[PDB]
Length: 299
Ligand SMILES: N[C@@H](CC(=O)O)C(=O)O
Image (cartoon, rainbow, N blue to C red; front, side, top):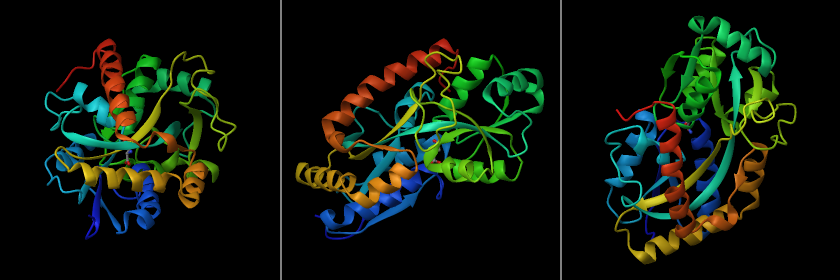
């Protein structure tokens, strides 16, 4: 192992934030894996369809999952998300931690986060919020945003924030929370309005955006960690090979440069099964409590 290419499933549309991470990582893992990694995009239901696909795939090491913190929210959002977060997989390791930006279409009237809150409260019924479906990173942040503002908004789900971004750029949807691996490009060129970040400290590549925390939203912190998993029952030597390849992929300079430019923190020393298992163990109950408090129930 591996004696043929390894398929890496990204549960979202090509060209978006997780796809960007996946394609860079696929390249960086190659020298150590000793085979090419082929990215497959499988969007739908906030990432649960793609996650489920890998959960049900042959445990031979030729199907692996690259998925983000939505892996941990979906079990509190769906009566049956299609997988069991603690047992459906053999965890390989953590990958990156990506902050989010609150953005709007380029001609959205407010120019800052204070004015945004005021505008959304006053004009709520005229405003659409985009996300990548229940279970997505943009869904989690969007939920937190409308809760913090005390509003209910028309909410439009997409198979990823790549198609959502298309509509935002096209002025077909108004407001979105999305990861810097997808938004940096559009923010720095001035193509979208940018209001705030969801990190505890400012994003150094986007230094003029205040955190939500410093903007008055105490504890409004969202970091979209990403993990890599194989299906339950994948042989230990195969998991071992995947761990070694992931570690080498994260330690690679080209990968790290691209991640740095996109505002992603590389979790270089946390690319091991135990770290990912611990992350999932902590995160599922954390988001469960958040949704419970927001009155957001399983469906
Ligand atoms: N990470 C997703 C977007 C999201 O979950 O909000 C994507 O790659 O499209």
